Length: 342
Ligand SMILES: Nc1ncnc2c1ncn2[C@@H]1O[C@H](COP(=O)(O)OP(=O)(O)O)[C@@H](O)[C@H]1O
Ligand SMILES: [Mg+2]
Ligand SMILES: [Mg+2]
Image 1 (cartoon, helix red, strand yellow):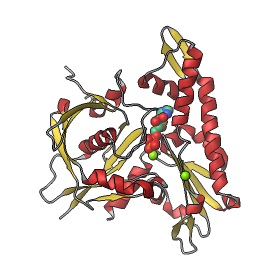
Image 2: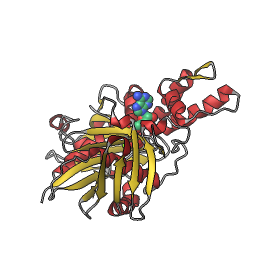
Image 3: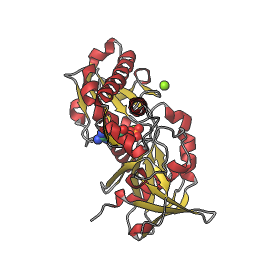
Protein backbone atom coordinates (compact mmCIF):
# COMPACT_ATOMS: atom_id res chain seq x y z
CA UNK A 1 0.00 0.00 0.00
CA UNK A 2 2.31 2.77 -1.26
CA UNK A 3 1.72 6.52 -0.86
CA UNK A 4 2.52 9.53 -3.04
CA UNK A 5 4.04 12.56 -1.33
CA UNK A 6 3.27 16.17 -2.31
CA UNK A 7 4.92 18.89 -0.25
CA UNK A 8 3.04 22.20 -0.21
CA UNK A 9 4.28 25.43 1.54
CA UNK A 10 1.31 27.72 2.04
CA UNK A 11 2.07 31.42 2.09
CA UNK A 12 0.14 34.66 2.27
CA UNK A 13 2.39 35.78 -0.58
CA UNK A 14 3.28 32.76 -2.76
CA UNK A 15 2.05 29.15 -2.79
CA UNK A 16 5.00 26.81 -3.27
CA UNK A 17 4.70 23.15 -4.09
CA UNK A 18 6.67 20.07 -5.03
CA UNK A 19 5.84 16.37 -5.21
CA UNK A 20 8.21 13.42 -4.75
CA UNK A 21 9.07 13.46 -8.49
CA UNK A 22 10.82 16.86 -7.98
CA UNK A 23 8.21 18.77 -9.97
CA UNK A 24 7.79 22.18 -8.43
CA UNK A 25 5.18 24.89 -8.89
CA UNK A 26 5.02 28.39 -7.46
CA UNK A 27 2.41 31.11 -7.99
CA UNK A 28 1.05 34.21 -6.20
CA UNK A 29 -1.40 33.70 -3.33
CA UNK A 30 -4.19 35.67 -5.04
CA UNK A 31 -7.46 34.31 -6.42
CA UNK A 32 -10.22 35.85 -8.54
CA UNK A 33 -13.64 34.88 -9.84
CA UNK A 34 -13.23 33.00 -13.11
CA UNK A 35 -14.85 33.41 -16.48
CA UNK A 36 -15.02 31.90 -19.94
CA UNK A 37 -11.60 32.91 -21.32
CA UNK A 38 -12.53 32.63 -25.06
CA UNK A 39 4.02 26.08 -25.14
CA UNK A 40 2.17 28.48 -22.83
CA UNK A 41 2.79 27.49 -19.20
CA UNK A 42 -0.18 26.30 -17.24
CA UNK A 43 0.93 28.08 -14.06
CA UNK A 44 0.25 31.49 -15.70
CA UNK A 45 -3.21 30.46 -16.88
CA UNK A 46 -4.89 28.83 -13.88
CA UNK A 47 -8.56 28.94 -14.86
CA UNK A 48 -10.14 26.43 -12.52
CA UNK A 49 -13.42 25.16 -11.04
CA UNK A 50 -14.03 23.37 -7.74
CA UNK A 51 -16.85 20.87 -7.15
CA UNK A 52 -17.95 19.97 -3.63
CA UNK A 53 -20.55 17.95 -1.71
CA UNK A 54 -23.18 20.65 -2.43
CA UNK A 55 -22.57 20.25 -6.20
CA UNK A 56 -21.29 23.81 -6.26
CA UNK A 57 -18.94 24.53 -9.11
CA UNK A 58 -17.14 27.69 -8.01
CA UNK A 59 -15.09 29.31 -10.77
CA UNK A 60 -11.77 30.93 -10.10
CA UNK A 61 -8.69 32.41 -11.60
CA UNK A 62 -5.67 31.97 -9.38
CA UNK A 63 -2.03 32.98 -9.60
CA UNK A 64 -0.60 35.21 -12.27
CA UNK A 65 -3.95 35.04 -14.09
CA UNK A 66 -5.89 36.39 -11.09
CA UNK A 67 -3.12 38.96 -10.48
CA UNK A 68 -3.93 40.50 -13.91
CA UNK A 69 -7.60 41.17 -13.01
CA UNK A 70 -9.45 44.23 -11.63
CA UNK A 71 -11.18 42.23 -8.91
CA UNK A 72 -8.69 40.50 -6.63
CA UNK A 73 -8.15 38.47 -3.57
CA UNK A 74 -6.58 41.12 -1.39
CA UNK A 75 -2.82 41.08 -0.93
CA UNK A 76 -2.39 43.66 1.81
CA UNK A 77 -5.94 43.41 3.19
CA UNK A 78 -6.37 39.62 3.42
CA UNK A 79 -7.52 38.82 6.95
CA UNK A 80 -5.28 36.19 8.54
CA UNK A 81 -7.28 32.94 8.66
CA UNK A 82 -5.93 29.43 8.41
CA UNK A 83 -8.94 27.81 6.70
CA UNK A 84 -10.68 30.20 4.32
CA UNK A 85 -12.09 30.10 0.82
CA UNK A 86 -8.83 31.34 -0.66
CA UNK A 87 -6.53 28.97 1.22
CA UNK A 88 -8.80 26.16 0.05
CA UNK A 89 -8.63 27.22 -3.62
CA UNK A 90 -4.89 27.88 -3.30
CA UNK A 91 -4.29 24.58 -1.56
CA UNK A 92 -6.38 22.66 -4.09
CA UNK A 93 -4.73 24.46 -7.03
CA UNK A 94 -1.27 23.55 -5.77
CA UNK A 95 -2.38 19.93 -5.27
CA UNK A 96 -4.16 19.82 -8.65
CA UNK A 97 -0.95 20.86 -10.37
CA UNK A 98 1.29 18.38 -8.52
CA UNK A 99 -0.97 15.27 -8.79
CA UNK A 100 0.14 12.91 -11.61
CA UNK A 101 -2.23 11.43 -14.20
CA UNK A 102 -1.69 7.66 -13.67
CA UNK A 103 -1.72 6.99 -9.92
CA UNK A 104 -2.48 3.29 -9.18
CA UNK A 105 -5.44 1.97 -7.22
CA UNK A 106 -3.16 1.42 -4.20
CA UNK A 107 -1.25 4.74 -4.25
CA UNK A 108 -2.89 7.61 -2.34
CA UNK A 109 -1.82 11.24 -1.94
CA UNK A 110 0.13 12.19 1.19
CA UNK A 111 0.34 15.97 1.78
CA UNK A 112 3.14 17.49 3.85
CA UNK A 113 2.49 21.09 4.89
CA UNK A 114 2.75 23.25 7.98
CA UNK A 115 2.50 26.56 9.81
CA UNK A 116 5.07 29.16 10.92
CA UNK A 117 7.07 28.18 14.02
CA UNK A 118 5.00 29.73 16.85
CA UNK A 119 1.76 29.62 14.78
CA UNK A 120 1.91 25.81 14.79
CA UNK A 121 0.56 25.16 18.30
CA UNK A 122 -2.26 27.60 17.74
CA UNK A 123 -3.33 26.33 14.32
CA UNK A 124 -2.18 22.71 13.92
CA UNK A 125 -5.69 21.35 14.45
CA UNK A 126 -7.52 23.90 12.30
CA UNK A 127 -5.15 23.05 9.43
CA UNK A 128 -5.50 19.32 10.08
CA UNK A 129 -9.27 20.00 10.15
CA UNK A 130 -9.39 21.71 6.72
CA UNK A 131 -7.30 18.88 5.26
CA UNK A 132 -9.57 16.20 6.78
CA UNK A 133 -12.59 17.88 5.17
CA UNK A 134 -11.12 18.06 1.63
CA UNK A 135 -13.74 16.44 -0.64
CA UNK A 136 -13.40 18.42 -3.88
CA UNK A 137 -12.83 17.77 -7.59
CA UNK A 138 -10.49 20.45 -8.97
CA UNK A 139 -11.10 21.12 -12.70
CA UNK A 140 -8.63 22.88 -14.96
CA UNK A 141 -11.11 24.13 -17.57
CA UNK A 142 -8.64 25.38 -20.21
CA UNK A 143 -6.36 22.32 -19.84
CA UNK A 144 -8.77 19.45 -20.24
CA UNK A 145 -7.90 17.70 -16.94
CA UNK A 146 -9.29 17.39 -13.42
CA UNK A 147 -8.17 15.93 -10.09
CA UNK A 148 -9.90 14.74 -6.91
CA UNK A 149 -8.52 15.87 -3.58
CA UNK A 150 -9.53 13.67 -0.69
CA UNK A 151 -7.42 13.18 2.39
CA UNK A 152 -7.17 10.04 4.43
CA UNK A 153 -6.67 10.95 8.08
CA UNK A 154 -2.96 10.64 8.87
CA UNK A 155 -2.38 10.33 5.20
CA UNK A 156 -1.35 13.94 6.01
CA UNK A 157 1.50 15.29 8.14
CA UNK A 158 2.13 18.76 9.55
CA UNK A 159 5.58 20.13 10.41
CA UNK A 160 6.36 23.54 11.90
CA UNK A 161 8.52 25.62 9.56
CA UNK A 162 12.22 25.77 10.36
CA UNK A 163 13.56 22.29 11.04
CA UNK A 164 12.95 21.02 7.49
CA UNK A 165 14.67 23.91 5.73
CA UNK A 166 17.68 23.54 8.05
CA UNK A 167 18.08 19.76 8.18
CA UNK A 168 17.86 19.47 4.40
CA UNK A 169 20.59 17.77 2.33
CA UNK A 170 19.91 19.46 -1.04
CA UNK A 171 19.88 23.13 0.02
CA UNK A 172 22.53 22.53 2.76
CA UNK A 173 25.82 20.72 3.32
CA UNK A 174 24.90 19.06 6.61
CA UNK A 175 28.44 17.71 6.82
CA UNK A 176 29.67 21.30 7.38
CA UNK A 177 26.81 22.25 9.75
CA UNK A 178 27.48 19.46 12.30
CA UNK A 179 30.03 21.13 14.56
CA UNK A 180 30.11 20.49 18.29
CA UNK A 181 28.75 23.10 20.71
CA UNK A 182 27.69 25.61 18.05
CA UNK A 183 24.40 27.07 16.91
CA UNK A 184 22.84 27.31 13.47
CA UNK A 185 20.23 29.98 12.70
CA UNK A 186 17.52 30.29 10.05
CA UNK A 187 15.92 33.61 9.10
CA UNK A 188 12.92 32.78 6.84
CA UNK A 189 11.62 36.21 5.75
CA UNK A 190 8.12 35.64 4.41
CA UNK A 191 5.21 37.78 3.42
CA UNK A 192 3.20 38.37 6.64
CA UNK A 193 5.51 36.74 9.23
CA UNK A 194 9.27 36.18 9.67
CA UNK A 195 10.65 33.00 11.29
CA UNK A 196 13.83 33.03 13.36
CA UNK A 197 14.76 29.48 14.32
CA UNK A 198 18.00 28.22 15.80
CA UNK A 199 19.27 24.74 16.64
CA UNK A 200 22.04 23.93 19.12
CA UNK A 201 24.41 21.18 18.00
CA UNK A 202 25.16 18.58 20.68
CA UNK A 203 28.65 17.27 21.33
CA UNK A 204 27.56 14.05 19.56
CA UNK A 205 26.60 16.04 16.43
CA UNK A 206 22.88 15.79 17.22
CA UNK A 207 20.82 18.99 16.73
CA UNK A 208 18.47 20.38 19.39
CA UNK A 209 15.83 23.06 18.99
CA UNK A 210 16.35 26.18 21.11
CA UNK A 211 12.84 27.56 21.62
CA UNK A 212 14.34 30.46 23.58
CA UNK A 213 16.49 31.75 20.70
CA UNK A 214 13.65 31.39 18.23
CA UNK A 215 10.46 33.30 17.49
CA UNK A 216 7.93 33.95 14.76
CA UNK A 217 7.80 37.69 14.17
CA UNK A 218 4.18 38.59 13.50
CA UNK A 219 4.61 42.26 12.54
CA UNK A 220 7.71 42.01 10.30
CA UNK A 221 7.60 40.58 6.79
CA UNK A 222 7.65 41.78 3.20
CA UNK A 223 4.12 43.06 3.64
CA UNK A 224 5.58 46.06 5.51
CA UNK A 225 7.28 47.18 2.28
CA UNK A 226 4.04 46.76 0.31
CA UNK A 227 2.15 49.03 2.73
CA UNK A 228 4.92 51.65 2.91
CA UNK A 229 5.01 51.74 -0.90
CA UNK A 230 1.20 51.87 -1.16
CA UNK A 231 1.23 54.93 1.06
CA UNK A 232 4.25 56.35 -0.72
CA UNK A 233 2.33 56.04 -4.00
CA UNK A 234 -0.89 57.80 -3.02
CA UNK A 235 1.17 60.37 -1.08
CA UNK A 236 3.41 61.10 -4.06
CA UNK A 237 0.42 61.00 -6.41
CA UNK A 238 -1.51 63.63 -4.42
CA UNK A 239 -4.41 62.53 -6.61
CA UNK A 240 -6.11 60.21 -4.17
CA UNK A 241 -5.31 57.36 -6.54
CA UNK A 242 -4.41 53.79 -5.52
CA UNK A 243 -2.73 50.98 -7.37
CA UNK A 244 -4.27 47.61 -7.97
CA UNK A 245 -2.37 44.51 -6.87
CA UNK A 246 -0.61 43.93 -10.21
CA UNK A 247 0.68 47.52 -10.05
CA UNK A 248 1.56 47.56 -6.34
CA UNK A 249 3.52 44.31 -6.70
CA UNK A 250 5.41 45.77 -9.67
CA UNK A 251 6.01 48.93 -7.63
CA UNK A 252 7.73 46.77 -4.98
CA UNK A 253 9.97 44.88 -7.40
CA UNK A 254 12.01 47.93 -8.54
CA UNK A 255 10.14 51.02 -7.34
CA UNK A 256 9.17 52.07 -10.88
CA UNK A 257 5.63 52.22 -12.25
CA UNK A 258 4.19 54.00 -15.29
CA UNK A 259 0.91 55.55 -14.11
CA UNK A 260 -1.29 57.89 -16.14
CA UNK A 261 1.50 59.23 -18.33
CA UNK A 262 3.78 59.80 -15.33
CA UNK A 263 7.03 57.99 -14.56
CA UNK A 264 6.60 57.24 -10.86
CA UNK A 265 10.04 56.62 -9.30
CA UNK A 266 9.83 55.58 -5.65
CA UNK A 267 13.07 53.59 -5.61
CA UNK A 268 14.34 55.88 -2.88
CA UNK A 269 11.46 54.87 -0.59
CA UNK A 270 11.73 51.22 -1.60
CA UNK A 271 15.36 51.12 -0.51
CA UNK A 272 14.46 52.81 2.75
CA UNK A 273 11.58 50.36 3.36
CA UNK A 274 13.91 47.41 2.82
CA UNK A 275 16.62 48.78 5.10
CA UNK A 276 13.92 49.53 7.68
CA UNK A 277 12.38 46.04 7.51
CA UNK A 278 15.86 44.51 7.52
CA UNK A 279 17.01 46.54 10.51
CA UNK A 280 14.09 45.29 12.58
CA UNK A 281 14.63 41.65 11.66
CA UNK A 282 18.35 41.95 12.56
CA UNK A 283 17.45 43.59 15.86
CA UNK A 284 14.97 40.81 16.74
CA UNK A 285 17.56 38.15 15.88
CA UNK A 286 20.22 39.92 17.98
CA UNK A 287 17.56 40.27 20.69
CA UNK A 288 17.15 36.51 20.90
CA UNK A 289 20.84 35.63 20.45
CA UNK A 290 22.83 37.44 23.12
CA UNK A 291 26.54 36.73 23.39
CA UNK A 292 25.62 33.31 21.94
CA UNK A 293 25.81 35.01 18.54
CA UNK A 294 29.56 34.39 18.59
CA UNK A 295 28.84 30.67 19.00
CA UNK A 296 27.20 30.24 15.58
CA UNK A 297 28.76 28.38 12.65
CA UNK A 298 26.19 29.50 10.11
CA UNK A 299 23.25 31.88 9.89
CA UNK A 300 21.33 31.11 6.71
CA UNK A 301 18.53 33.36 5.60
CA UNK A 302 15.74 32.17 3.29
CA UNK A 303 12.27 32.78 1.83
CA UNK A 304 11.20 35.22 -0.84
CA UNK A 305 11.96 38.10 1.52
CA UNK A 306 15.36 36.65 2.40
CA UNK A 307 16.14 36.54 -1.29
CA UNK A 308 15.40 40.24 -1.86
CA UNK A 309 16.85 41.47 1.47
CA UNK A 310 19.97 39.27 1.63
CA UNK A 311 22.41 42.17 1.10
CA UNK A 312 20.95 43.98 4.13
CA UNK A 313 20.27 40.91 6.24
CA UNK A 314 23.86 39.77 5.81
CA UNK A 315 25.04 42.67 7.95
CA UNK A 316 23.98 40.76 11.09
CA UNK A 317 27.20 38.74 10.73
CA UNK A 318 28.67 39.26 7.26
CA UNK A 319 31.49 36.68 7.06
CA UNK A 320 29.29 33.88 8.52
CA UNK A 321 25.79 34.19 6.95
CA UNK A 322 24.56 32.64 3.71
CA UNK A 323 21.52 32.44 1.43
CA UNK A 324 20.00 28.95 1.03
CA UNK A 325 20.22 27.51 -2.49
CA UNK A 326 16.47 27.80 -3.32
CA UNK A 327 15.10 30.29 -0.78
CA UNK A 328 11.41 30.04 -1.55
CA UNK A 329 11.26 26.24 -1.87
CA UNK A 330 13.43 25.80 1.22
CA UNK A 331 10.65 24.78 3.58
CA UNK A 332 8.78 22.85 0.88
CA UNK A 333 11.86 20.70 0.17
CA UNK A 334 12.24 20.14 3.90
CA UNK A 335 8.61 19.08 3.88
CA UNK A 336 9.41 16.58 1.07
CA UNK A 337 12.41 15.04 2.80
CA UNK A 338 10.47 14.79 6.05
CA UNK A 339 7.35 13.27 4.52
CA UNK A 340 9.19 10.85 2.22
CA UNK A 341 11.18 9.30 5.12
CA UNK A 342 7.84 8.64 6.82
N1 LIG B 1 11.83 39.01 -7.74
C1 LIG B 1 11.27 39.57 -6.64
N2 LIG B 1 11.35 40.91 -6.40
C2 LIG B 1 10.79 41.49 -5.32
N3 LIG B 1 10.12 40.81 -4.38
C3 LIG B 1 9.97 39.46 -4.49
C4 LIG B 1 10.54 38.75 -5.64
N4 LIG B 1 10.23 37.44 -5.48
C5 LIG B 1 9.52 37.33 -4.32
N5 LIG B 1 9.37 38.54 -3.74
C6 LIG B 1 8.68 38.85 -2.47
O1 LIG B 1 8.71 37.72 -1.61
C7 LIG B 1 7.39 37.34 -1.25
C8 LIG B 1 7.32 35.82 -1.25
O2 LIG B 1 7.60 35.33 0.06
P1 LIG B 1 7.44 33.77 0.41
O3 LIG B 1 8.81 33.13 0.41
O4 LIG B 1 6.33 33.20 -0.42
O5 LIG B 1 6.95 33.87 1.94
P2 LIG B 1 5.52 33.32 2.44
O6 LIG B 1 5.83 31.84 2.60
O7 LIG B 1 5.30 34.05 3.74
O8 LIG B 1 4.51 33.62 1.36
C9 LIG B 1 6.47 37.99 -2.29
O9 LIG B 1 5.21 38.42 -1.73
C10 LIG B 1 7.24 39.19 -2.79
O10 LIG B 1 6.91 40.39 -2.06
MG1 LIG C 1 7.21 31.15 4.10
MG1 LIG D 1 5.82 35.77 18.74
